[PDB]
Image 1: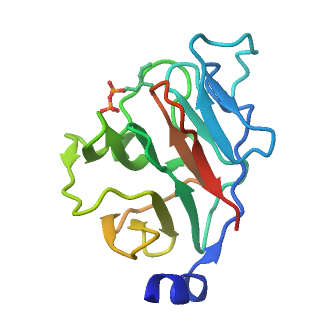
Image 2: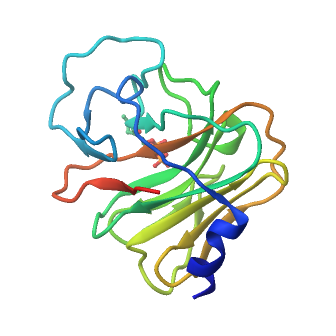
Length: 187
Ligand SMILES: C=CC/C(=C\COP(=O)(O)OP(=O)(O)O)CO
């Protein structure tokens, strides 16, 4: 459909690979750096400045300061996941609420069937069909971050008219221990 035929004409396909130096020590990044899982217990890793030490987050390796970009994430049958973008300068040490005011523009799924945007306060989304693959779209200049069901092209949510000033990274968060990983589709 139009989603597949037009996406690359409007947005540059980003080749997103996960940065293991950023990942909370309870997360495992796959060898190909496209997939993340959770461990039962935190692994023994350095508390280097780029690493999230409280939130169960990991970033892409590259950030964006201009332009239109997109990437796609296979969420599959996971019961919990959150994805989107965040500012380079978010607080990675200690707790902050993941909200736009704190530099995070994310949405996702909790408790198997509760879709939300991570706003303040959180907003519930009503999705006709549960997505298995989600497209994340950034237009830096217009300030729009938009999420689509990447199989049927349906709209999930858009953060409108944000005034970005910092570089933006893809961000991924998983809280639960489940058999299915969260995985980036290669460009
Ligand atoms: C270690 C805390 C669990 C965690 C996130 C939960 O944060 P939260 O209670 O503010 O909930 P929410 O961000 O609304 O899902 C790791 O990213």
